[PDB]
Image 1 (spheres, rainbow over the protein chains, first blue to last red):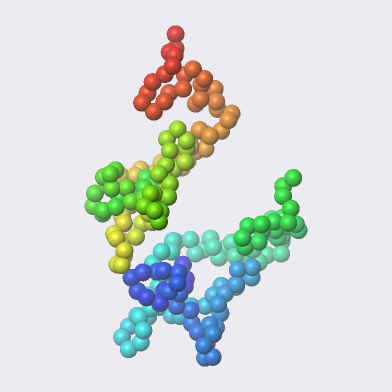
Image 2: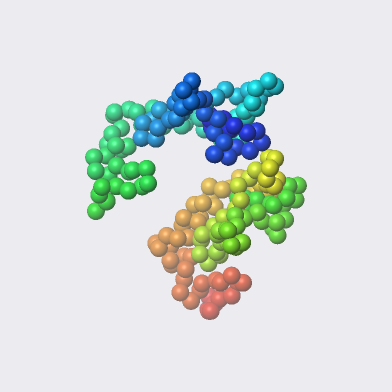
Length: 99
Length: 99
């Protein structure tokens, strides 16, 4: 919903236009376990420079997603989102089960 | 209400833009006796790919249909939806009648 595609028309995930640093590496590639979101180049496809177009697939749920992120970073909801042994990894595997 | 026509403007059932596999067959054709819904190609009419427009005949009853689908698979409604000798098959034929 926020990241921009490097090529207009299509919004393929392999054409992510992340703002790269001076050394070459991206400034903020983003993290999944951490709730920090990645940084993206500004949406401006004018003449002179390369044409970068915004995401063409996002819905209108930016506000609920921001609320969910705020809940995820809240230490008062650990009993739901950061359970002791029933934490879910990125691939969907927990230490224990419901039994 | 979900499956999208392969061509915009017309919503013919024969133009179902389903998601096909590498071999050529669709990923999920869908079943009637089973409650699995068919898979469809994502709605996208941008450049590069074909123009995919969702069907315009769909009503606003997605939630009641989802509820009915959930009820159909509930084993607590066997006496209603899955009577032993009064189960209606696809073409509307019953083994026995109300007599």
